Image (cartoon, rainbow, N blue to C red):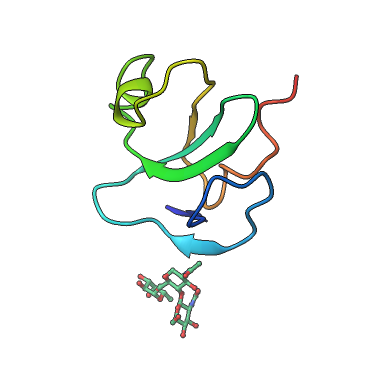
Length: 77
Ligand SMILES: *[C@@H]1O[C@H](CO[C@@H]2O[C@@H](C)[C@@H](O)[C@@H](O)[C@@H]2O)[C@@H](O[C@@H]2O[C@H](CO)[C@@H](O)[C@H](O)[C@H]2NC(C)=O)[C@H](O)[C@H]1NC(C)=O
């Protein structure tokens, strides 16, 4: 999956790059402050496998399966 991967927790990442290996679900987390951007698994995209790996909790991780679907446009209802 090709998604944007930033070196820091910014709220406007625009660097498109292929996702590392062992990654089939793009992840777009938003802890009301920083829009995390990283390649995540579809099995680890639950309400415990992400808030634990990042060592956080209050956040809305949204996994996707489209070349670049973790952008900042899928968490504003
Ligand atoms: C992500 O990687 C792809 C590499 O795709 C390869 O080429 C495809 C045509 C297909 O054969 C895949 O199975 C291959 O793995 C990048 O796409 C190519 O990248 C090369 C080198 O950068 C470039 O010369 C080609 O023209 C590109 N072709 C296409 C269709 O993209 C792609 O750009 C990478 N994306 C990012 C954000 O890095």
